[PDB]
Amino acid sequence: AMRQRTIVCPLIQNDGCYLLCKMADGQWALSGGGVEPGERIEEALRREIREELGEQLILSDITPWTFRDDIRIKTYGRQEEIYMIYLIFDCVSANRDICINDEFQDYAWVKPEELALYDLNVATRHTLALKGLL
Amino acid sequence: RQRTIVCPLIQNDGCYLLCKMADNRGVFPGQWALSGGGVEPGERIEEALRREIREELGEQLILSDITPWTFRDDIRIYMIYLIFDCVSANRDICINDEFQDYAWVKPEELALYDLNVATRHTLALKGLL
């Protein structure tokens, strides 16, 4: 009866720079969220983007890239293991118009050569390294 | 409503494994496909993949590498397909319920087989057709 979820995450690129979001108190990460009952995976992705990054952002292309699993121990206040499947999509944005919500404290469009300067969380480092960007 | 399916694109020494579905009858031939298995609650996706392979292709098949490739979705129930690139150390196959025959196929001959829709889309995306 372990908690298990499928998570959709977009790696958003514009004019060669990648979007990173700073989690509210707090590391830098890709955005993303869970797929809810009755939703298709891309529907969940677009919903998460609207919610977290706003309605001004315009995506030109969304393409499934790769997936992996992860196990995390979350502390709500009790501790529980959560098994996740990460579905990572390559996204190209037509613009850079971002409007953040309370899940994020800040955001940045970062050139690949500067990604390593950021205090990224573990999952984000893994994803970027697999893409050959880090 | 929700199902996660794991599928291996298995290759050995330049050839890819295709399996002929037992699913279908009369004059309508069973189509050729990649193996596909469900993931039980609490089961890791790679463990589910290895279980599917053991169940439908036999325990004798040794995998030298299993690497996530890509995913997509489909409907039949809403499915999420998780497709892995795999390399087998050998070509020993022993089939059971899902399949009635198998073949190791050169990439240039894959298109000659009557591939099911999902398999066709997957091989096309891989650049093999």
Image (tube, coloured by chain):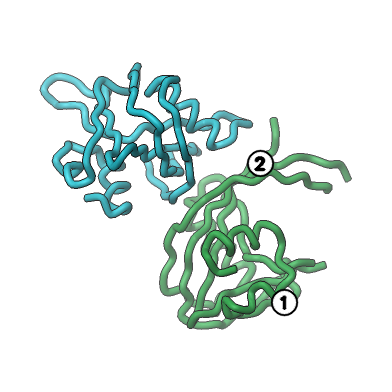
Chain colours: A green, B cyan
Spatial CA span between label 1 and label 2: 28 Å
Q: Do the residues labelled 1 and 2 touch (CB within 8 Å)?
A: no
Q: How many numbered circles are shown? A: 2
In the figure, is residue B104 to the left or right of A131? left
Who's the residue at 20% across and 42% down the image? Answer: B110
Q: Mark 2 lies on which chain?
A: A
Which residue carries the number 2 mark?
Answer: A83
Who's the residue at 36% across and 37% down the image? Answer: B10
Q: Toward the viewer: A65 or A38?
A: A65
* Amino acid identity at mark 1: Asp
Residue placed furthest toward the right: A77
A87 relative to B35, above or below: below
Label 1's element? Answer: strand
Q: Toward the viewer: A131 or B2?
A: A131
Task: Look at the image and tell me in which quarter the C terminus of chain A lies.
Answer: bottom right
* Amino acid identity at mark 2: Tyr
Residue B91, image quadrant:
top left
Residue placed furthest toward the left: B27
A41 relative to B44, above or below: below
Q: Toward the viewer: B18 or A27?
A: B18
Residue B18, image quadrant:
top left
| Residues packed near mark 1 inside 10 Å, few (<14), some (14 to 19) or many (20 plus) | some
Label 2's element? Answer: strand
Q: Mark 1 lies on which chain?
A: A
The answer to whether residue B1 of the structure is visible from this angle is: no
Percent position of residue A129, x then y? 58, 62
Percent position of residue A26, x then y? 79, 67
Which residue carries the number 1 mark?
Answer: A106
Who's the residue at 78% across and 68% down the image? Answer: A24
The answer to whether residue B69 of the structure is visible from this angle is: yes
Task: Look at the image and tell me in which quarter the N terminus of chain A lies.
Answer: top right
On residue B87, which mark appears?
none
